[PDB]
Image (cartoon, rainbow over all chains, first blue to last red; front, side, top):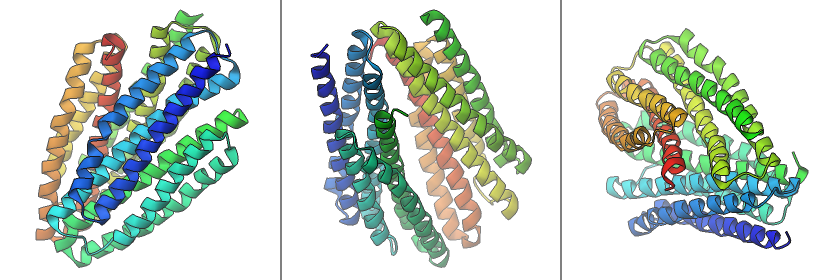
Length: 211
Length: 209
């Protein structure tokens, strides 16, 4: 041991580094959509490969660590929280990358007459949820983690009311359907990003509380 | 010991996979046939699926508690735990398809989309069955064929969407019904990505990368 806990901090810090890269993808995707910025949107998709390769590198790392002799219960909880959470980070990065596709599409089609304030609002919240879940993991802080998980309720709630606004608007202005659907798909991806931040928070709870 | 609990966990996985395939089949059929009873069946199983997932995940964690496994054994258990998340996501997307089927029963049938739902639905159903069969037999050839087919589903989804959108502008009164077909199609495409994910676990376990 006891350099087993070095290699353990190394995989913890690799998680954090992945999370940081993914959080920046969320930031850039949202800005891309709002700013009708194709270049920024493409830059986000091109990161998604590095993110997938980070996830693979972390999974193998968890494998090697585990392979060396049985971990104590708390350590096992940590490795398990890491390997499940890189899946969440990967799915966050993939959703970011879908938002960036919507961004490009809206550049081609013209802006939606509705939904930008909602995208920005939900996006900034869900990006916060990601920072907080990572900060919570980084500090074994199951208090913060709990509130993240709880805030997901209000995000899903905001999503359903924005959907209402946007569907009823589509029925009033059918010419805008293609553009409104793009905002709606982007909002659905932002909601999922918040669902995954919540999952990573719940893993931090399990890690800390033991359950 | 490992061999025994591995077969235990593998045995629960295959049962879970079997229900989920039936869920997808029931949910696609519910939509095409306007059959809300069958959609109800999809939603019922979904609770069992989530149970199986939780159980299977606990078993994996206990197995990881126990030994010190060879790397290759760790890979396998970690991949099993991943694959049950995919199976749960598939189950959940099937439930969404069922919900859409119910709404459509209420609204009367959409003027458009059922041909594409049958088409994409049957392909994605096949992808799941093959992904699971490939996993059951560690057949990496089959796995790779599944993963690569996803691109054609995504392509078919994108052309279906374009045509359904333009149709909704030609006929605004169908908006609510057509949106339901679109949401269902979104779930099916998602089911395809999850079958692709399971097939890719097989490729990784067999070929390394």
